[PDB]
Image: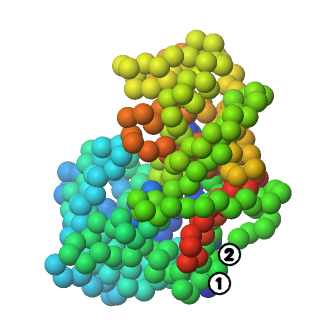
Amino acid sequence: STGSATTTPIDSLDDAYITPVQIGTPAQTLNLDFDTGSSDLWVFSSETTASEVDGQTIYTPSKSTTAKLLSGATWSISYGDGSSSSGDVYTDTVSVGGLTVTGQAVESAKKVSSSFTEDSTIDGLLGLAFSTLNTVSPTQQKTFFDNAKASLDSPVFTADLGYHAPGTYNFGFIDTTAYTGSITYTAVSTKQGFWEWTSTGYAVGSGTFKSTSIDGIADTGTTLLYLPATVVSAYWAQVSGAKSSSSVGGYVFPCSATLPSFTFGVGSARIVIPGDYIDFGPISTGSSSCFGGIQSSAGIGINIFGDVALKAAFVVFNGATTPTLGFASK
């Protein structure tokens, strides 16, 4: 089997992407944030505290003839941005782009933190990291990809995120029309539960490539590119007036600037992030200070190849017995 679904930016900055997902019988379609940095499929629901729901579409398990309470199971997750959610668990039929999994754990939120409530466009998350990170207790549950894998034509999914435009998540096949050149594959460590790999270096604009190992994670659920402070300083030093602002929370730059590109290495191959992809717009409405799309990872503990980086590539998440990542230009 295969599946193919369009993913759409939630706003004009590409702060996140939403993909429609069918849950239950008859189908209830929710727009989920596909997150290769986590491993829980959780949704706003009829069980979510009413004051914490503000415009989201909810899953109502009592209206699904295929929903079953997973008795005794609870979940609770906290994300790198400080947001969180928790609740109980049903199993139900879940379909993405024509690919159907029966018996998928659907984690129903009883509580969500303010940032989820405040984002009316995201109805939940669909985790695509390794199932070892799934938070369901006392019986850990599998991701949608893990459940689908054996049925897929090939044990892979691909992320093709658009810049200020829709893109595609495919399951079970590699669309050879969706990229240019060849796909360069690189090793993955699953030891932390992430799609963790090592970039071979970087360049800023037309500058020379610096060969240096940068361990980090391919994370579709993180907006920006978070890299070591040395790398980030070298980038922003090429932008007149750019500076790190403790009050804003990262590098800012004059909105009048034209940003240089940023290149990252995948083996001997190179992925070029155009400068425009690094502009996240005014820090507050009407400001002439703009927020940068490349930020330091120094306070995180891990480097994160988030959407800023991934949207410059066609990315293969290869879930073969030994997982790997592939990157192609597009």
For the residue carrying disc 1, how many other residues have a C-alpha within 10 Å: few (<14), some (14-19), or many (20+)? few
Side of 245 where 172 appears, left or right = right
Q: Residue furthest front?
A: 212
How far separated are the C-alphas under marks 1 and 2? 7 Å
Q: Amino acid at mark 2?
A: Phe
For the residue carrying disc 2, how many other residues have a C-alpha within 10 Å: few (<14), some (14-19), or many (20+)? some
Residue 153 — which label?
A: 1
Q: Residue at x 49, y 24 (%)?
A: 251
Q: Quadrant of residue 186?
A: bottom right
Residue 301, x across and y down, in percent: 39, 42
Work out whether 201 lies above or below 18. Answer: above
Q: Residue furthest right?
A: 181
Q: Residue furthest left?
A: 72
Can residue 215 be seen here?
A: yes
Can residue 126 be seen here?
A: no
Q: Amino acid at mark 1?
A: Asp
Q: Residue furthest top?
A: 241
Side of 321 where 202 appears, left or right = right
* Quadrant where the N terminus is found in the figure: bottom right
Display colour scheme: rainbow
Q: Mark 2: which secondary structure?
A: loop
Side of 263 where 65 appears, left or right = left
Q: Residue at x 38, y 20 (%)?
A: 246
Q: Quadrant of residue 138?
A: bottom left
Q: Nearer the viewer, residue 241 or 189?
A: 189
Q: Which residue is mark 2?
A: 173
- CB atoms of marks 1 and 2 within 8 Å: yes
Residue 82, x across and y down, in percent: 30, 43
Residue 145, x across and y down, in percent: 49, 74
Sequence-wise, the earlier of marks 1 and 2 is: 1
Work out whether 71 lies above or below 281. Answer: below
